[PDB]
Image (cartoon, coloured by chain):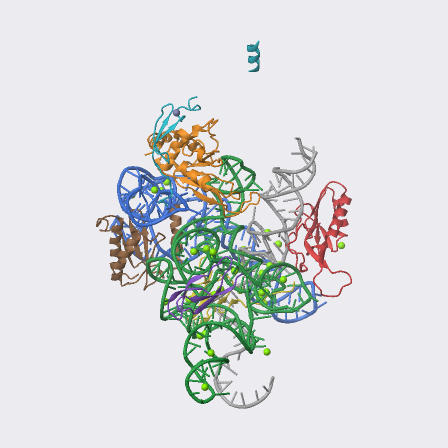
Chain colours: A cyan, B red, C purple, D brown, E yellow, F orange, H green, I blue
RNA sequence: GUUGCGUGGUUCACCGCGGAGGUAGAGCUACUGGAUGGCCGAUGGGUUACUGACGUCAGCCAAACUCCGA
RNA sequence: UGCCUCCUAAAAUGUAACGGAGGCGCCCAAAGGUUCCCUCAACCUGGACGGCAAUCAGGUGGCGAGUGUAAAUGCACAAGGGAGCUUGACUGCGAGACUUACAAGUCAAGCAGGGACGAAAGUCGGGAUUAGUGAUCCGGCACCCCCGAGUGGAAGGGGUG
RNA sequence: UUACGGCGGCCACAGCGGCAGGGAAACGCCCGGUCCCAUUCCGAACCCGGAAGCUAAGCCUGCCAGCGCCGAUGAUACUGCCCCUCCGGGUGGAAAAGUAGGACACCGCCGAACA
């Protein structure tokens, strides 16, 4: 049922701190949505006891 | 021997008629006791016969008791008139028909096995015989 | 708790039907659209 | 597969209370994505007495969309039924929901002579 | 103990081949132990009465035992 | 016109065909629906889910979710049959594609101490499930306007017939495994 | 039971044909319970030599068990 | 000590005992009517809090779940689960039957009026069925205007609920 | 007459499962959600408009007894009526289970292609 049930869902714009920018349609956020980290910058996407004894002595 | 539960506490007497149709052959051991007449075998008599067999063989061998006393029998108190409700269960009974195999035995030595089964038979309120798995 | 109630025609006030209800589940007088033999049609009815 | 099974279930459920006889036959419809089919059954001996479908000259006698084609095939079945001597039927949804193509077919069959 | 209810006299009242009148009671029952066939109505308390004159006929209708009346 | 959908239709469909020797294009796996529910527990207690779950799942997804009611009663949870205990939404279509993109791209990485979703959480047929714990990474909700935090778990249903096929499809789609 | 007035084979017996059954018996991996011996052995028990779930292979029982059935 | 269900009860119906087991003296304004849609329990796997068991997803599952309330007979075609609209939980009847010492009790196609739901065909005179109840007398209340102790009224009686 | 799509009869000897094969029309998946209509959320479903793709699935054909189903003859249990004290016997019926075996259905009407 679609009369007054679902929230607004219209075109938005994602901008990231690194610069990877795309656009989909999200909810209530009116236009642009600014993000600090994305899939294009976050890590995991971009990659001795005796040793300590000897480096101490 | 007593069943853990019974759905119906007080029951009609089991009917004493017909030849047995199931459990009429030795199935677990080499020697068995076969009933030749109807009767109500009690858990008391079953334990007496089992103890007789075990104390005769004294060691080794295996004894199977392929009947269970699950049919109950009631009894009114001692000095009471007739008819004021059915009495409370006081015996547990197995319904034995002719041809039924009561006990089964495996033992190496023929004579000792047969003597043990005769010991058992003299405890039961039935005429019984000893049969073998051919 | 479930008394017998009687329904009267709105127009002619004839006591036409008697029935039961739960006074707690229905603390207010019923309205049903029953057939009135006097008026000859279906009319609204209400408790008395 | 699930669709086929569910439609069969709905058809049987409505079929419990609707038979169709010699004087008042049953009007079965079978609506696919592309076409529509109809026949009169007389469920006492399982004998179709008239039938029309969307594989005809109807396939090109197209004044628009599938609803218009259903209207046309309804006009055909009504006339074929009157020719066979029937004038009253019971409509069979076939497990579908009454509305759209099927309702258009049924209405056309109503104003073209069938009484149901 | 000691209580019981009245015997309700259920069962089949007209057997196969009997010629009945319209309105005959054929089967008193609880639930549909038998189901109604052609010319047989069920009844409020599952009574399977007759709608037409004819002869009673029992049969099987894909798992259900049914009662019918042939004109 | 969801970019993840066109990237799928453009490269993933024939990459999967190259990987598994599908003799028919109809056999190529795809994601059919995505299901998100909260699974609230405060049903017997405080009876509030009208905004704890509905008025934020609306924000995360874009459509109003459905309120689920207990099917039976359990005493050890004070649960009585017929009362609201869960809130579920079913994303499907381009909204589902857009939600998958918005998740994998900007939401999933934002999880604190995120080190990669497990690849062993498939059902055995090809369907993947994983859970969250808060009204975080979805930027749509604001922590300034939430009651108590609560998580969710997401089901990604695929037409894949085996776990390896489903895992390949999700890896191509951009799900970070480890 | 007898008797008056009506009716007249409608009654009953045998043969044939059309019907509904759940008794006797039997059977139970067909259900609800009971229950013997193996094997696997859940837990509980002190690495488990005690208990023995659920299963599974053979043998059995029941007025208020029935996939059956005179 | 009345009523309902089962066994005894001997395969039609019926059948006793201070024989063996249970329920009832209500509930529902929707848990009634109609139209449309759906299939459960249990088990397996995966999944934040979450565990044997809350919600989700996917498998397997033909009835082992459920049915307002005992049991029996039924019900998956659903009589089980959900939704929309409604008041037939009608008025005047009722051929023909079951049961039966009598009094009672039970079923009923179909006709008419005026309606509900349905596109129609059609279903609907409460509830899956069987308990939830009390003869006659004597009174109370509302309506019809039937009788009205010389006449007109009235009292009082009568009828229908 | 053959061989495909529907509507029924019948309700496992027909079911479940396994392995192969097919797309002329048709049945299907399929592509979309402007329109009637729809979701206790979702164009998934129901409905509407189409025809890019494909027999992968449904559907259809062939072969499999694996699970399930059916299943005699004979014998037995039981039993009506007699004889008979019982034990038993005569005469008339006759199971359930098990075995041999059967079985991967059959029939009718309509439409299309072929005729
Ligand atoms: Mg036996
Ligand atoms: Mg002795
Ligand atoms: Mg209310
Ligand atoms: Mg009774
Ligand atoms: Mg017979
Ligand atoms: Mg019985
Ligand atoms: Mg017996
Ligand atoms: Mg059993
Ligand atoms: Mg029996
Ligand atoms: Mg009886
Ligand atoms: Mg009887
Ligand atoms: Mg009898
Ligand atoms: Mg009492
Ligand atoms: Mg109801
Ligand atoms: Mg229902
Ligand atoms: Mg309703
Ligand atoms: Mg009433
Ligand atoms: Mg009458
Ligand atoms: Mg009328
Ligand atoms: Mg009526
Ligand atoms: Mg009633
Ligand atoms: Mg009831
Ligand atoms: Mg008196
Ligand atoms: Mg006067
Ligand atoms: Mg007066
Ligand atoms: Mg009257
Ligand atoms: Mg083709
Ligand atoms: Mg679609
Ligand atoms: Mg195919
Ligand atoms: Mg194929
Ligand atoms: Mg034979
Ligand atoms: Mg047999
Ligand atoms: Mg077969
Ligand atoms: Zn970034
Ligand atoms: Zn009125």
Q: Position of residue B76 (x, y in %)?
A: 74, 60
How far across and down, in percent of the image, does residue F66 sit? Answer: 43, 43
Q: Residue furthest top?
A: A57
Q: Is residue D21 above or below residue H137?
A: above
Task: In this rendered view, identify the residue nearer to me: D76 or B92.
Answer: D76
Image quadrant where one finds the C terminus of chain D:
bottom left
Quarter of image, res H117: bottom left
The answer, for residue F110, to whether it is visible in the render is yes
Of D52 and B86, the residue lying toward us: B86
Spot occupied by residue A42 in the image (x, y as percentages of width and height): 42, 24
Question: Residue A30 location, x and y as percent?
Answer: 35, 34
Compared with B38, F49 (above or below) is above
Left or right of I58? Residue D50 is: left
Query: Is B133 rendered above or below residue E16?
Result: above
* Up/down of I42 relative to B124, above or below: above
Q: Residue at x 77, y 42 (%)?
A: B58
Q: Is residue D110 left or right of residue B92?
A: left
In the displayed structure image, the side of residue F49 where residue A21 appears, left or right: left
Quarter of the image with the N terminus of chain D is: top left
Residue D77 seen in this snapshot = no
How many circles with numbers are drawn on the protein? 0
Residue visible at 37% across and 67% down in the picture: C41
């Amino acid at each position: 049922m679609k009369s007054d049930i679902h929230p607004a869902y219209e075109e938005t714009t994602v901008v990231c701190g690194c610069g990877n920018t795309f656009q989909t349609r999200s909810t209530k956020p009116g236009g642009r949505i600014v993000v600090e980290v994305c899939s294009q910058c976050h890590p995991f996407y971009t990659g001795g006891r005796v040793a300590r004894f000897e480096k101490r002595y | 021997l007593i069943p853990r539960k019974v759905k119906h506490r007080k029951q009609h007497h089991p009917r004493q008629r017909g030849i047995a149709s199931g459990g009429t052959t030795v199935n677990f051991g080499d020697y068995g006791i076969q009933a030749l007449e109807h009767a109500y075998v009690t858990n008391r008599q079953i334990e007496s016969a089992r103890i007789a067999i075990n104390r005769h063989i004294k060691r080794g061998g295996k004894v199977w008791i392929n009947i269970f006393p699950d049919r109950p029998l009631t009894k009114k108190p001692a000095e009471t008139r007739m008819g004021s409700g059915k009495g409370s269960p006081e015996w547990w009974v197995a319904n034995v028909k002719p041809g039924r195999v009561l006990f089964e035995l495996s033992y190496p030595n023929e004579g000792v096995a047969r003597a043990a089964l005769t010991r058992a038979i003299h405890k039961l309120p039935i005429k019984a015989r000893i049969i073998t798995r051919e | 708790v479930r008394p017998k109630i009687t329904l009267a025609c709105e127009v002619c006030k004839h006591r036409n039907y008697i029935t039961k209800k739960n006074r707690r589940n229905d603390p207010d007088r019923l309205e049903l659209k029953k057939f009135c033999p006097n008026c000859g049609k279906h009319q609204a009815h209400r408790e008395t | 597969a699930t669709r086929r099974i569910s439609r069969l279930r709905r058809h049987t459920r409505l079929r419990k209370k609707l038979s169709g006889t010699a004087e008042r036959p049953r009007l079965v419809v079978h609506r696919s994505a592309r076409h529509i089919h109809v026949q009169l059954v007389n469920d006492l001996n399982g004998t179709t007495v008239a039938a029309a479908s969307s594989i005809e000259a109807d396939v090109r006698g197209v004044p628009g969309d599938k609803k218009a084609r259903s209207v046309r095939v309804g006009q055909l079945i009504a006339e074929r039924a009157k020719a066979a001597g029937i004038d009253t039927v019971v409509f069979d949804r076939g497990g579908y929901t009454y509305g759209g193509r099927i309702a258009a077919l049924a209405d056309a069959a109503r104003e073209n002579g069938l009484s149901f | 103990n000691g209580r019981d209810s009245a015997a309700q006299r259920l069962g089949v009242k007209r057997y196969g081949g009997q010629v009945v009148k319209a309105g005959e009671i054929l089967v008193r029952q609880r639930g549909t132990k038998f189901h109604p066939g052609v010319n047989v109505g069920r009844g409020g308390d599952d009574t399977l009465f007759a709608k037409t004159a004819g002869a009673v006929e029992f049969g099987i209708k894909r798992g259900r035992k049914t009662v019918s009346i042939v004109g | 016109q969801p970019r993840l959908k066109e990237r799928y239709r453009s490269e993933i469909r024939d990459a999967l065909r190259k990987q598994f020797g599908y003799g028919n294009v109809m056999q190529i796996p795809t994601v059919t629906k995505v299901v998100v529910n909260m699974g609230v527990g405060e049903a017997a207690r405080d009876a509030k889910l009208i905004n704890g779950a509905v008025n934020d799942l609306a924000l995360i997804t874009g459509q109003k979710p459905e309120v689920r009611r207990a099917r039976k009663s359990i005493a050890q949870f004070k649960l009585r049959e017929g009362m609201p205990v869960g809130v579920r939404v079913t994303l499907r279509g381009d909204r589902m594609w857009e939600f998958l993109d918005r998740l994998t791209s900007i939401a999933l990485p934002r999880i604190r101490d995120f080190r990669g979703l497990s690849p062993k959480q498939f059902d055995g047929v090809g369907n993947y499930t994983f859970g969250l714990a808060e009204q975080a990474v979805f930027h749509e909700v604001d922590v300034d306007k939430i009651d108590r935090v609560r998580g969710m778990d997401i089901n990604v249903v695929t037409s894949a017939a085996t776990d390896d096929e489903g895992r390949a499809l999700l890896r191509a789609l951009g799900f970070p495994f480890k």
